[PDB]
Structure formats: C-alpha cells, structure tokens
View 1 (tube, rainbow, N blue to C red):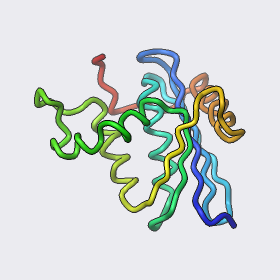
View 2: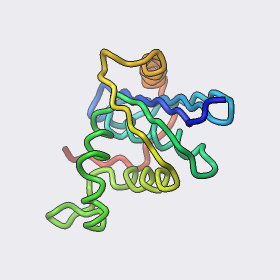
View 3: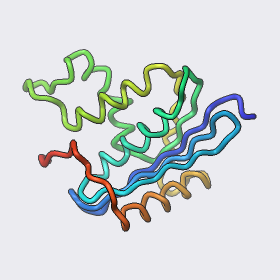
View 4: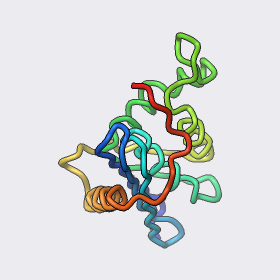
Length: 155
C-alpha cells in the first residue's frame, strides 16, 4: 500500500445559491473510497469545504496526507485566513461570525489530527483523480438529495 494517505476533492455548484455537489476520492488502508452527494440549495464555496470534510472525517487516527484540489475558496481559507480566524475566535474584524463558520470549524476539527501536504492544482491541469471528482460533483449537483442546513444568504 501507499505510505501516504491521498485525498482528492472537488465542489461544484452553478447557482449562488443553487443545486450543488461534492466529490472526494480517498486512498486509505489499501482501499479507494469515493464519496459524492448533491444538495438542493448551496454554494460552490460550501461544496469545496464539504468534500474535504467528508474525506478527512473518514480517517480514524492521525495520518500523513496529501490533499489535492483545484478548490480556490478552500485554498484561500487554508493559506490566507484560518490562522487569523482562530486567533479572532472565528469572528470577522467587525465582530460577526465568519462566513461559513459552521463548515470551517468542522473542517478545522477534521484536520486537527493530520499532517497534511496541500496540492493546489489548477482547474485545467488536474490529475485523473481531480477530473473524476469534478465529474462526480457535477453529476451530484444535477441530482441533489440533501439539505445544506447551515447555508445562510449573504454575499
């Protein structure tokens, strides 16, 4: 087996908000798990978070992970914001809860155990697994079955 855990993720959503979906591929314990699900009313940004959350939550002990995705919102948060958000108690500078706090906190909890190497691939230069996630997420968006309970509307 692979000696690092590999995760690939994608989120898709045409509307803002609209029907959306996520997909993730996880190589863990010598197996390849694939997760995908669609939501009636959500955003692309929230689907990018969900995909990473669901894959990372499947890990049951601390792991060494390489997570690969073209997800720009996820990338922006991890590389530019999450440190500062935690410092500020998950508030904006104007004292309100940060946008998508529900999912950022859930993701933060899911990342806590793991040593993650992030691979920020470009949308047109993904690996086959990135392409597969994208196709899965788009199909999930076209067939939504779940409610994005935590979505709220400002923009």
